[PDB]
Structures are given as structure tokens and as C-alpha cells.
Image (cartoon, coloured by chain):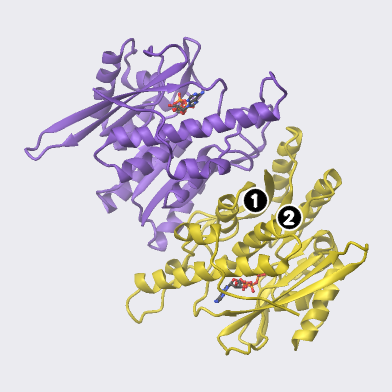
Chain colours: A purple, B yellow
């Protein structure tokens, strides 16, 4: 039995945050203790949204409720989108305490700050969080899944080539996490502009005390839509598949990405079905077809192959 | 697809309310929009607990967030334990509006108000809701899953025999819902004192335009432990199987009760395993093994047979 503490947002409708994380982890065999950092009607990509946000003090109370009953015992910790610096500090405190309690605990972190629109890079999170993630969160993480912009923000270096990207990933390894995946990047692909490039790096221990970094690269088809909650889903499935494949980042990333691709392909198909023929689907019609993809999440058909560098 | 609006509690750890309803319904192929009426660390059976309660105003805003985006379209509505009169009135208003929008909507309601400890009957809910449930909720409900004590409260008449139980169920049919299932009772079983009796009743329209009431009985073995969330799970799975078998309450209840049986058998097994040999398992060790029972929930092996009266 593998228990994951997932502290993420909750939407009444749709799949972002914990809604995008609990179902896949449960279908993949993980107990999930879920702290819903917000309760919104839907994700903010909609025209409107209503709801409430959990205060950090409220998050602390929940964790203390678990601690008092001696149930604050976890094998993993999963976090994602946060706009409250204090809440991030609370999460870091909790992770440190759980790691004192269990040295084998794995903290998977999606450090969400921004993304590259067109060629420009833009942050959708308060700026005062960049120090935190860099100085307090990522140092305590074991798996991080940033995108190129976030990788650049964390390392302070811009990425212009794949070799520069892996130098940045080595810097991130040095900051803390032994597994680093750059989920998206503006690096060119060998198949064309319709494919996106993602890279992975896992540093592993040797018998002599030394350490070897395994590097992998993946090219994925781009689906022509903007989806929300994809990162959150990606980090959950990466957690699961790295757990089953702790020494093979290649296989874990292959399974994860294939499952993402399956989910997105089904989602874009059903979205264009709901919308008129040749019509732009709305955020509501682009909600991930999570339920309808259960089997794909359980045992994905491999549709991408990672190259070991 | 089939979308369910489920307004129930949420626990960080464990399976009650939405935690006990979302996963099975999603695994059974239903889109689920979930409104967490509360967020607690764990259910109140533990030694300690902390969390927050959603206000009715907050519930209204979530529903309005869905409405403004033209996303308040549902095939089912599912509710359970509530302690606030205003919250129940809000739920009733929402159900009324959704039924105005769609006459085919089915409201599944577990009218949770109390249960029978030993032979005595005791209430878990403020008294001012019993009028509400009787006068405002049940009238707009289509499926209800009360226990003997709740059925007695709603009907105002005590149940001493199975014939009296079906008279009470006919009264409840008269109050609104065309399907009524009494999930637990103190009626004797021909197989022993370790069997629990559940009864069902569905009013169905015939081809001639008239209506026939189908009644069924189920004898199920007691598992000697106290579980939490079982009503929530029961109602969710009953919703699913009645959707699959709209004219066969027999099969729907057989599947539902079999899944419950599988889940509870696995749960008591693993709970006694976690606890010492010959040790009473704790509330924490008796949390439903929801994830590990996925497959049984997907397609339960029939282990009980309902007799058609
Ligand atoms: N339109 C898309 N086409 C193909 N893959 C996508 C698409 N959107 C998301 N993905 C997949 O989802 C992963 C994460 O994407 P996103 O998270 O949406 O983008 P991102 O830039 O990583 O944003 P983050 O990591 O959450 S802040 C990517 O690495 C892809 O695997
Ligand atoms: N100890 C048990 N032994 C066998 N079956 C059980 C047990 N507890 C729960 N169940 C199953 O789950 C259902 C339990 O429903 P209950 O939780 O008893 O409903 P209730 O507690 O009587 O009141 P409500 O309003 O439904 S929450 C039963 O119909 C059984 O299917």
C-alpha cells in the first residue's frame, strides 16, 4: 500500500489539481489523502469562476488533525498550483517534518509559475514566489516537473539549446531533486513543428559511492488546443510510473506521456464533436475526458519512445 | 455521458461522503461534479478531527458559477449527510431549478438523520431538518435510501414487521420518490441473527398506462465492525446500477449489495491484519479499502439473491 498526500486545488466541475490527480492515482493503486487548497466552481480558464480559497492556517489545522491521530504517515507528497506564499511555506514545513519521520519519502513537485506564450515568457503567479520555490521548495523536492520557462526561472539561466537545457537540469539536480523532467520546451524537434520536445534526467547512486545521470528525450505530437490541468495530471502519473520503475526514467516517462497523449487525443476529439464542425471549442468543451480514459491511464498503449542520451 | 452533481462531505483521509461516492461513480463511467459540503481531516469516529464547513451562501455561489457558464446541466443529483437547514433548502432549490431545466433528472437522496443502536433509535442530526426532509426534500426526490429509523421518522409510524415496512415504503412512495430502498433494518432473517435485511420498492409505469409496484427483499451477512461511509457508497452504487437497470430493481440492488459485500469483506480482512491478532481494529484501520476494491466495484460477482415478493 502506497499512500500519497496531495495538496492541490479542487474544482466542482472539471479536472485540475486534485480532480486531475486523485482519480488516476487511485485507478493506479495508490491511497490518496487529498487536501483541497481551493474550492472553485471550475478552473480559471472559464469566463467566470466562483469559490473559496483555503488559508494556510486552515491547511495547518487539517494536517494537525491527521497528526494527532498518528495518521500523518505518507510515502509520497504531491503539490502543484499555489498563489499564496504562506501556503507554500506551510507545505515545505510539512514536507520537512514528514521527511524527518520517514527518510524514504518522495516529494513530487510541479513548480507552477508561468509558461511561454508564443516566444515570450510570462508568469501567472506572484513574483515573490520565485525565491520560495528556488530557496525552500525545490531544495526539499525529489521529483520536479517544470517547463522550460520555469526551469529558466529557477536556474536563472535561459535555455537556447538541448545541451544548455541539460546543464540547467544538472543545476536543478544540484538544487535538490534527483529526478527532473522538463515537460515542455521550445526546442526544435526532428519531426517538425507539430511535435513538442520534453527532456528527463535522473541521477542515481553507484556501489562505489558515485552517481550516474541518465538522460532521455521525448518528442510528442502537439494537440491544437489549450488544456488546463494537464500538468497536474502529468505529475500524478509520473509519480505512479516512477514508483513502479524507480531505476528506469525512460519507461516511466514513456508510460506517462503516452497516457497523456491518449487522454488529450480523446479530449480534443470529443471537444470538436461537442462544438460545431470547424468551430473553436470552449474551455468547458475541452475539459479532460478523465473518466472515459480510465483504461488508457491504467495500462497505456505506448505511442512515444524516449531516446536515451 | 451521464453527469452527476454530488453535494457531500470531503475528508482528507478516508472514504465518506464524496470520497466514498466519486471514485466508484467515476470507475462506473459517470462524470461527477462534486461540491464538498465540508473539508475535515477524517470522519468523526476518530479520536480527533479538524476542518471547515461550507456555508449555504458558498454553495449558492458555486452553483451560480456553474450556471453563469451554462454548465449547470446534469442527469443526476446525489446528496447525503447535512446538519444545516439552510444548506438543505439550498439543495432543494437547486434540484427544483435543475428539474425545471430537465424533467428527466433523477434526484438520489440518502436522507441521513439517525440509526438504531441496539434496539434504541438515536438521531445524529438537528431536529429542525426532519420537517425539511419530509416536506421539501423527499417530495422532489426520485430515489431514497433510508434506514429503518429514518423511514420511520419520515413516515411517522413505527415498523414492527416486513408488511408494516412495505406500508411505510408505500407512504414514502406517496411522498415522492418512485424508488425506495431501506438499507438496513432490525427485521429477523431466516438464515440467522447475523443477516441484515434490506428491502426495496419501485413504482413503475406499465404499457397500459397504469403503475405496478415491484418489491424485493435481501438478506446479507453482517460484518462485525462499524464502518463509516457505507451509506454514501451504497447510494452512489445504487444510482449507477439503477441507471444501468432502470426497470430491474432486483438486479440493481443485487449488484449494489454484492459490491458492498466485497468491499466490506476486504476491509475487515485488511483491518484485522493491520491490527494485532485478536485485536479490535481501530476506526483508522477500518477505513474502506476503496482503491483495492475497484474491480469488484466495476463488475461485482453476485453473492446475494433478492427474492421478488
Ligand atoms: N496541447 C498539448 N499537446 C500535447 N501535449 C500537451 C499539450 N498540453 C499539455 N500537454 C502535455 O502535458 C504536459 C504538461 O503540459 P502543461 O502542464 O499543460 O504545460 P507545461 O508547460 O508543463 O505547464 P506546467 O508544467 O503545468 S506549469 C506536457 O509535457 C505535455 O505532455
Ligand atoms: N456491518 C455491516 N455488515 C454488513 N453490511 C453492511 C454493514 N455496514 C454497512 N453495510 C452495507 O452497507 C449498507 C449500510 O447502510 P447503512 O450505512 O447502514 O445505512 P445506515 O447507516 O443504516 O443509514 P443511512 O441513512 O443509510 S447513512 C447496508 O445496506 C449494507 O449493504
Looking at the image, residue A229 sits to the left or right of residue A164; the answer is: right
Towards the viewer: A194 or A140: A194
- Check contact, mark 2 vs mark 1: CB within 8 A: yes
Q: Given the current orientation, which residue lies at the most extreme front position?
A: B207
Residue B42 visible? The answer is: no
Badge 2 element: helix
Total marks placed? 2
Q: Residue at x 67, y 43 (%)?
A: B1
Chain hosting mark 2: B
Badge 1 element: loop
Question: According to the image, label 2 marks what residue?
Answer: B87
Quadrant in which residue B72 is drawn: top right
Looking at the image, residue B133 sits to the left or right of residue A20; the answer is: right
Compared with residue A299, is residue B209 higher up or lower down, i.e. above or below?
Answer: below
Q: Quadrant of the C terminus of chain B?
A: bottom right
Towards the viewer: A95 or B273: B273
Q: Residue at x 68, y 18 (%)?
A: A278
Question: According to the image, label 1 marks what residue?
Answer: B54
Q: Residue at x 43, y 40 (%)?
A: A236
Q: Residue A146: x and y, percent?
A: 39, 27
Looking at the image, residue B7 sits to the left or right of residue A130; the answer is: right
Amino acid at each position: 500500500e502506497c499512500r500519497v498526500l496531495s495538496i492541490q486545488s479542487h474544482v466542482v466541475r472539471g479536472y485540475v489539481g486534485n480532480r486531475a490527480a486523485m482519480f488516476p492515482l487511485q485507478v493506479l493503486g495508490f491511497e490518496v489523502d487529498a487536501v483541497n487548497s481551493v474550492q472553485f466552481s471550475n478552473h480559471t480558464g472559464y469566463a467566470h469562476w466562483k469559490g473559496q480559497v483555503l488559508k494556510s492556517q486552515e491547511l495547518h489545522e487539517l494536517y494537525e488533525g491527521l497528526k494527532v491521530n498518528d495518521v500523518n504517515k505518507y510515502d509520497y507528497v504531491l503539490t502543484g498550483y499555489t498563489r499564496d506564499k504562506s501556503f507554500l511555506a506551510m507545505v515545505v514545513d510539512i514536507v520537512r517534518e514528514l521527511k524527518q519521520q520517514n527518510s524514504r519519502l518522495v516529494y513530487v513537485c510541479d513548480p507552477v509559475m508561468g509558461d511561454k506564450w508564443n516566444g515570450e515568457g510570462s508568469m501567472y503567479v506572484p513574483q515573490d514566489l520565485l525565491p520560495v520555490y528556488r530557496d525552500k521548495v525545490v531544495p526539499v523536492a525529489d521529483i520536479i516537473t517544470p517547463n522550460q520557462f520555469e526551469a529558466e526561472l529557477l536556474s536563472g539561466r535561459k535555455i537556447h539549446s538541448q545541451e544548455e537545457a541539460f546543464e540547467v537540469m544538472d543545476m536543478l539536480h544540484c538544487m535538490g531533486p534527483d529526478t527532473v523532467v522538463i515537460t515542455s520546451s521550445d526546442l526544435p524537434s526532428s519531426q517538425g513543428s507539430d511535435y513538442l520536445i520534453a527532456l528527463g534526467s535522473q541521477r542515481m547512486r553507484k556501489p562505489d559511492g558515485s552517481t550516474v545521470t541518465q538522460r532521455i528525450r521525448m518528442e510528442m505530437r502537439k494537440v491544437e488546443a489549450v488544456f488546463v490541468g494537464t500538468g497536474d495530471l502529468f505529475a500524478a502519473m509520473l509519480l505512479a510510473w516512477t514508483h513502479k520503475h524507480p531505476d528506469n526514467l525512460k519507461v516511466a516517462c514513456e508510460k506517462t506521456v503516452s497516457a497523456m497523449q491518449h487522454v488529450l487525443q480523446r479530449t480534443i476529439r470529443c471537444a470538436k464533436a461537442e462544438a460545431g464542425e470547424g468551430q473553436k471549442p470552449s474551455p468547458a468543451q475541452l475539459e479532460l475526458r478523465m473518466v472515459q480514459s480510465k483504461r488508457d491511464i491504467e495500462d497505456p498503449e505506448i505511442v512515444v519512445q524516449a531516446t536515451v542520451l
